[PDB]
Image (cartoon, rainbow, N blue to C red; front, side, top):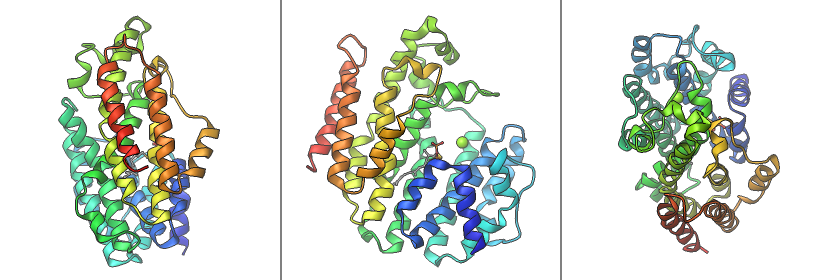
Length: 341
Ligand SMILES: CC(C)=CCC/C(C)=C/CC/C(C)=C/CSP(=O)(O)OP(=O)(O)O
Ligand SMILES: [Mg+2]
């Protein structure tokens, strides 16, 4: 089982966040989800390496899923740090993969291919529209939501009805991806080349140059745009509440709930916060421990989400050009929560 051990070891190095939450899952589901994550993590590593040619990515990505059945395949000159190691010693992942149930392998192979092609689409173009924003989030996060949902059903832990309509699963992925895209604006725009995800359709209403938000000079417009991004992410909350409330298994529930509650805490902190444009805004380690502790069942999770949702709303004024748009979004979220209390 050295292969699985490497997997969990690389997981811990490549992503401390997920590597903690994944431990909420029972061993069998956990192995499948851990391997699933590393496969996608490998894709991400190819998509994000800006020192390697795009034609190289459009070439390798589409057939990434095919390598899942080739225990000798690996990549040598891509990525930084442990990610690089993930690809070079990618054998451990494919081996572990070959020892998974037939149904788990197919979900993983299926999501891997669709995400890869989606990444290819956006490797050759920008995110101009809100539609673009949403679709890109779908490919790199919404699909993880689909995949996980299909792994839950396939495992037997959740009812087959869960996979009927995957819309809410996609919403779950979008809420997480969007909160991170919002939180990581500065860090992303400060890289070489600069990484940009905020959709032009949204930011062109406050500026002609996104890079202007880095200057205190345009602090007001940056914050108004930041607030419009938050409003856009809040659209997903009522759906996150529905998906979480449809879960019956405690392991699946905690694994699914924790990241969502963390996202809402981050979102409540970045909202109307100009610090977002010069540093990473993060929750305290104590709030994190508390979230991990209580998000084991629906009721407590709903109240923590309500609490954070109420903190977000409390942070604004009738002066802000969002107060209107944010208010009904907060009410929809809180309403959806009380709808299960
Ligand atoms: C359960 C369900 C239906 C949907 C959830 C969808 C999921 C799990 C999406 C993962 C997408 C994100 C935000 C990845 C960043 S890697 P990271 O999480 O390791 O670490 P970081 O964001 O850098 O802190
Ligand atoms: Mg990426």
